[PDB]
Length: 113
Length: 26
Image (cartoon, rainbow over all chains, first blue to last red; front, top):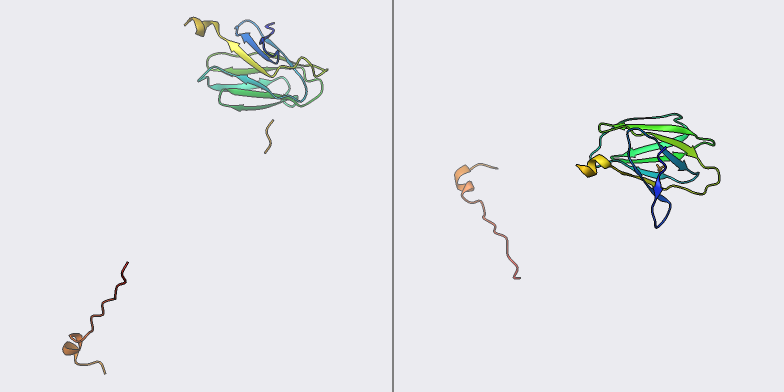
């Protein structure tokens, strides 16, 4: 389980180091739209939720927004592109605290290249 | 996520007036 590490300024914005062998535990709360970005020039192929009506999905280029829409929405998101495949264990938080506004990636292989 | 008579042909065609419009000084 890759738990995002938050920024030092506000713990609303978090970063995760991408990994083929692990999933991202996302703590989504009610009433917030959360922002996810891809690599530059990454072509989105398909996405598949465990529950299509539990979350709301709209994608623009390399930017992914997901939104809660139903109580007890605990499913997964598998958004796949040409470069790789993402895995998030979407979990609603009940108390509307410890939110996470935007998730960012740190890529080891690209940085090394 | 997001919201939302007429004869005399030759002499009479040489008598057709030439009317040139006047000008105004600018």
